Image 1: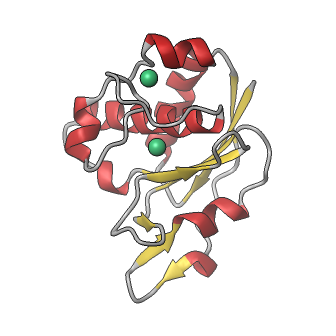
Image 2: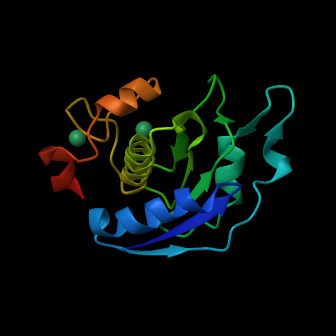
Length: 158
Ligand SMILES: [Zn+2]
Ligand SMILES: [Zn+2]
């Protein structure tokens, strides 16, 4: 397994956080692609947010590719989403916009958790109701409450 991180209008510190943590978590080689701007094609001026599905569909469909953006994103019927993944597919996107915080260590943990979550989906995992990174999070407060680790059931499936 290899993971390709596509920076899209996100600071380089956030990228380095994922580059350094993902490899051990997934026993995969991680590659950072040249940064680029998130495409204005995906911008929704009315909402001042980018559409997560539109961003996802512009990434190369190469398992596993994770786009990471600093911009706030939404999906159809959602105020906002933290991200979006192709379940059992190739691509996912993560926005760190809703995750920002002046507590640098907390921010690091949130970024890693939600990246791990999205990649879990790419690897075929659905939402989990155990104490598990694959738990759905309604808000960042919920992100803070779930662990960065897969429960024994989810770990056995990947
Ligand atoms: Zn999810
Ligand atoms: Zn689980």
